[PDB]
Amino acid sequence: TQQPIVTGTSVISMKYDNGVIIAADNLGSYGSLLRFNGVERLIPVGDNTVVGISGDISDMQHIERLLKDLVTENAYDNPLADAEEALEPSYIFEYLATVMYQRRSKMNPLWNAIIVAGVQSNGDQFLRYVNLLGVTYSSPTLATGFGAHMANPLLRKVVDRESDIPKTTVQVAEEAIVNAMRVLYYRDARSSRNFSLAIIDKNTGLTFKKNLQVENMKWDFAKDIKGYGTQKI
Amino acid sequence: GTGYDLSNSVFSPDGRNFQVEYAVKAVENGTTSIGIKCNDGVVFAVEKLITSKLLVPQKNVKIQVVDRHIGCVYSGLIPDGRHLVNRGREEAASFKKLYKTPIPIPAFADRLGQYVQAHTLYNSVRPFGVSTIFGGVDKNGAHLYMLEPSGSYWGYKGAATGKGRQSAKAELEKLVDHHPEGLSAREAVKQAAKIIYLAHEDNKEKDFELEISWCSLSETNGLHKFVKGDLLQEAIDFAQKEIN
Image 1: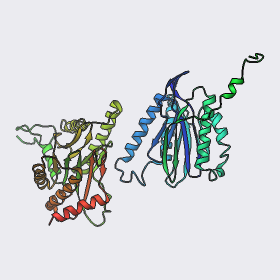
Image 2: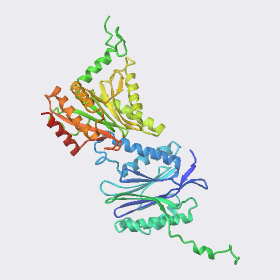
Image 3: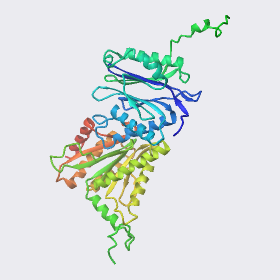
Image 4: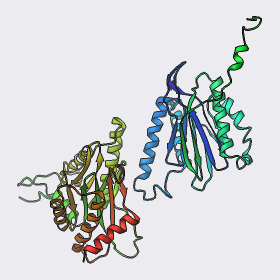
């Protein structure tokens, strides 16, 4: 049993017709201190999988080492390591889910919320979540922490059910994701303006965008607001 | 008296460990394999005797990778070889976990060295029946090594072991003399394919299959990779051509 120290906030994601999109800002909080700003919380595994992590950063780094090892180990005595026998997003997830549940079962959890996004070898999209309790679930859209409360409602307006997937394009999806990130920047006190976004498309492959920034924010209406009730000036 | 050769860690009257020496016999009785250090990497090649047409070609791979920057090939009892590589892998993983940086070739060599030497310390274990050629690129260059069943190892410019080690060594020595400036990864791959072909005369009875791998700072980015397709055939031909 422990307590998170340096933490990463929301991780949001959704799937579109040709793949999945996942994003997460670059902040590493220390309580209410916005302590670190160059933290990458999206971990690419191979070229068909990206793992988004929130929660304790020290544990995130541990999961990173684990993922690198998975790649190294899968390459051993594997002549088809970059072909038929490369790591599938589902393998990477089942692995992490296993670890997450074993650790909570030993009363020593990896204090994180994880979302594994990718495209299977047969082209199928992959989006599944696992957290410190070992709980897992899939949905056309998935978000952790604050994003679960504010991103999902927005992302679900694009893909409310399975049949909305084929009707959604990368442009629509990426736009929804970028807007959600802005909303989270407005209301989440542990969020950052800088973030990374990655797309895993069954045709274009893995696109990993770094250093994005929330833009087009509305703040002007603030000038009109004064006092907290009766004040006029 | 006698019987000094029935138990592993026993010193004979002349200070030898006969069981290690018998382990060597098992190595000399094995397929030939080599390693060539080039100007920015290393190349590994090995002879693969075609027992019969039934062996699916290209499937029974012998060269093994350790971590992501090291290659290992060996001659002798194959299972003993795998055993040693598994140890090397655990050994490399441990080093990376504590020091973050992937294990340096010299450091790695000693890990295998100590482990192998350990198997000559007790009569409850048997020495390793393989000589291993391995190496890769690291923070400061390329390194080639060869480890004997005694646990003895040194850095090499070129190395060979197995049935045709003499032919190979002869060839390697020529290369060393005619290239004081240094061979290139591209060249080494071909030269390696040739030596395996030449050294195959000491077993010319059975047909074989060529296998090459390399690790070059420029050609593979410092990662160990197998030579396949076009680059492979191009090397096979270069040999078939100079075999006549």
